[PDB]
Image (cartoon, coloured by chain):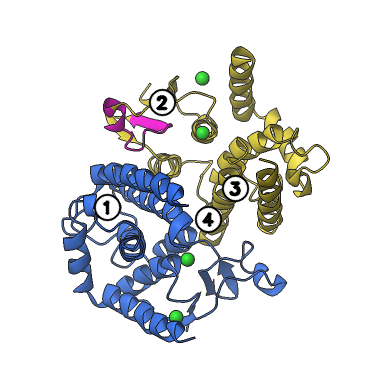
Chain colours: A yellow, B blue
Amino acid sequence: VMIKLHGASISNYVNKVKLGILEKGLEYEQIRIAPSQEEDFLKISPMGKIPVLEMDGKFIFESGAILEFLDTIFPQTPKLIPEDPWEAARVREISTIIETYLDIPARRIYSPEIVEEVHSTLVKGIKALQRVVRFSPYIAGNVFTLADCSGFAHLSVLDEELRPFYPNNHPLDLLNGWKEYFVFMKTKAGPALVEKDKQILKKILA
Amino acid sequence: VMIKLHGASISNYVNKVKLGILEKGLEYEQIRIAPSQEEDFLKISPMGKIPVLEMDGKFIFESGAILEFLDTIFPQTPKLIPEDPWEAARVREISTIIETYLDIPARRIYLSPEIVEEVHSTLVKGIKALQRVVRFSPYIAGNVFTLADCSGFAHLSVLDEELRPFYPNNHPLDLLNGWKEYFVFMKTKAGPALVEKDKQILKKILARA
Ligand SMILES: [Cl-]
Ligand SMILES: [Cl-]
Ligand SMILES: [Cl-]
Ligand SMILES: [Cl-]
């Protein structure tokens, strides 16, 4: 509609944005593309990454910037950024811990030495996350926020993608509240659609 | 003093926050500590990182969240996040590119000559991307100081110096059109000058162990 979301459902970062869009009840069309280094794509997305949000003939190309922007131009509940400034800091912190300290490192695994080195980094990252999450029932508290966008998109991937490498050792197993949060989020229409599209794509490609 | 900033002036993430505090004219005390995994520190800074902002016995421990917070509660000029939402997005994009695609890669090095070439092409890629969104007119995102100047001045100044040893005629930053002039302009300002000065004072002292 007024909004186009450029990028396939294979991308954690695309799914992050898609979650916030769906929860806001916004009309949008998802354009299913892969990242590209083609000059013409670099004009709208300088690093050649997805997702890219498009609206009013203009583009935003960082998933964080995108959701902060949607938050600002569509300020109605659910507010991706809480009105309470302390609660907002907690939400941004959770999203940053998940992306920078969990996902980035986990992207070394998606060799033996690395698996080991990576497993320890994730354990540390998970023990830190544990200190700021509430899961009551949402990741930062009792309402949906930007942190649920990052949390459901990134952690559902981490958990699944690493269940074979850490069969009895899964770092995310140390995150109290996660399995139950994951189940709860999947009962909601937005995250269920996000998960469905991802599963379809993964059955297709496999 | 209402605001306490925990972390030493040699950290670019501390300096990123310090630039924003100084530019708004806020009063703060800087508490010099180094990163740490002591259970005492982890209680206020889960990853053991600096900076941590302390106010009213409450702690915020990621530099981006700190500056978004300070800009919300202390909205006096400059607005680190512009009021125009499209301008705000561009400010956030610039800051992300500088931190995630320039500094994180660079930290692989400055913190295998093969690795030196991987990092080199990655940085050149990041710079050409950055070149696309910067304005330097005179600030990095336009005619007023923003969050992107905190990230820009804090990270790029460090990237510039710390990488000349590695890339003598090869420096990625030399590709950023306007950087040298911006860096000179910023140093004419009291806040950025003070950040550079505090960094210099501690470096000189540390060098003599
Ligand atoms: Cl798709
Ligand atoms: Cl991705
Ligand atoms: Cl210091
Ligand atoms: Cl640092």
Tell whether B182 sits left or right of A75: left
Q: Residue at x 33, y 42 (%)?
A: B125
**Residue A134 vs residue A162, the one in the foreground:** A162
Q: Secondary structure at mark 1?
A: loop
Q: Which residues are magenta?
A: A39-54
Q: Are marks 2 and 4 on the same chain?
A: yes
Question: Chain letter of disc 3?
Answer: A
Name the amino acid type tagged 1.
Answer: Asn
Q: Is residue A188 left or right of residue A176?
A: left
For badge 4, the amino acid type reads: Ala
Residue at the top extreme of this rendering? A204
The residues bearing labels 2 and 1 have C-alpha atoms spaced at a distance of: 35 Å
Quickly name the residue at label 3: A98
| C-alpha distance separating marks 1 and 4 | 42 Å
Q: Nearer the viewer, mark 1 or mark 3?
A: 1
| Nearer-the-camera pick, A180 or B199 | B199
Q: Amino acid at mark 2?
A: His
Q: Quadrant of the image for the N terminus of chain A? A: top left
Q: Residue at x 75, y 48 (%)?
A: A175
- Residue A78 is marked as none
Q: Which residue is mark 2?
A: A6
In three-dimensional space, the C-alpha distance between marks 1 and 3, rounded to whole angstroms, equals 35 Å
Instruction: Kindly check if marks 1 and 4 are in contact, taking CB atoms under 8 A apart as contact.
Output: no
Q: Earlier in the sequence, mark 2 or mark 3?
A: 2
| Residue A152 as seen in the image, left or right of residue B186 | right
Q: Which secondary structure, mark 2?
A: strand
